[PDB]
Length: 262
Ligand SMILES: CCc1ccc(-c2ccc3c(c2)-c2n[nH]cc2S(=O)(=O)N3C)cc1
Image 1 (cartoon, rainbow, N blue to C red):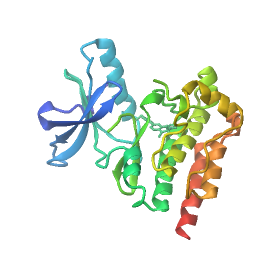
Image 2: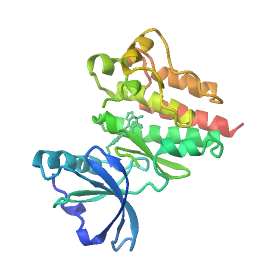
Image 3: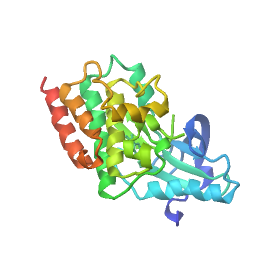
């Protein structure tokens, strides 16, 4: 649990305004002053209850976990401050949360851009799958936008998500890479719906009955039939029948190229 080579001196951080929230408290914009960059914009996770040591241990665990990963489409850990008030310093995704990015840009994003985002996320997810990493805090799962052509996996924003969960997770709290694939199928649907949430107006308790009746989220307007088909494969009832992330990443590439050939 050593953070020594990524421990940041506090005076190198200028804490700015609140820009969002994580499981443990508010996320702030900031500036980090280092030899590498005189003024780097950062996101700073704070912790409302880290005066409690059990809470503090769980919070800094988020940093220890993030440290082990390095991927173009996963929000990077810059460093930590492990003295009170404890902070986790992360890269700042300047364009905010993908959901609201998509809602305001329904007509200014080409279909190729939407497919690229799905592809980029699949590369990150296949990377994690190869590392045997099952991300446990499913309620915290998010996607942030670092540029027009770059999205990243994150666990903060800028209850269980039943409407996004695989049937075996809902029924039996089984969580595997195959349940992650089901949830990513939903994420893809949301991207192609320009940020609309699944099962709007449906009670959480009614979700499993619809799945078990054979019902699935409908093809989004203007969505390529091949891409919708890919989503439906993520939603095989039997987890063993779903594609692996390696296959999703291969299929999304072929779809992306085809849209660019149109
Ligand atoms: C840094 C540790 C970490 C934090 C969050 C995730 C993360 C974020 C978003 C995700 C996911 C993970 C994710 N894994 N499987 C399915 C999904 S998802 O819900 O579609 N999705 C967008 C992965 C690793």
